[PDB]
Image (tube, rainbow, N blue to C red; front, side, top):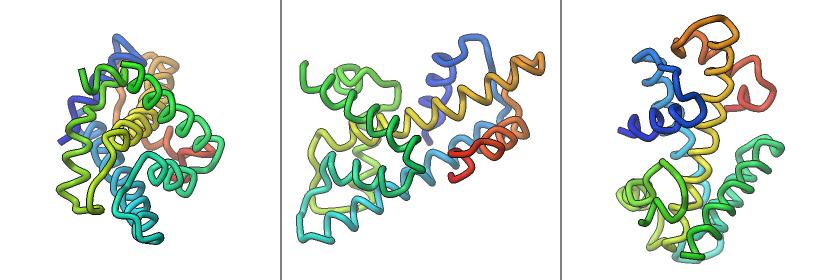
Length: 170
């Protein structure tokens, strides 16, 4: 499960907001869907040319190949930040994210998505997922505060993921 990273991301966009237990399952489902989609698409890219490696740029092209492209912009912007900020220098920490780089890369390779990956590829992918996770939790947490509630309920989640131009694409 990825539930710890979601909660940790929720604490950053909204320090004093909680989340119902199946609203969280909903968040775990979203993470795994969006991970499967991007990581499969970079897998195909990798074998579209006959490159063995899924690298940051296969992820990036997958990103611009899946997200609505104002959203993709911020996502690729976020994944590029995590990469350059990881080079300058731990592991996850150097990338300045809460979604574990090591665990994301371990999910990538137990999916056999390609031959091998750059160590800069799970950082990019954890950055992207952390960003969309933070967007969903950000807006939802806001609609909760707008309605005077301390917890993200599942129905708030869905009226937020729908009822938003880009996020409804996902």
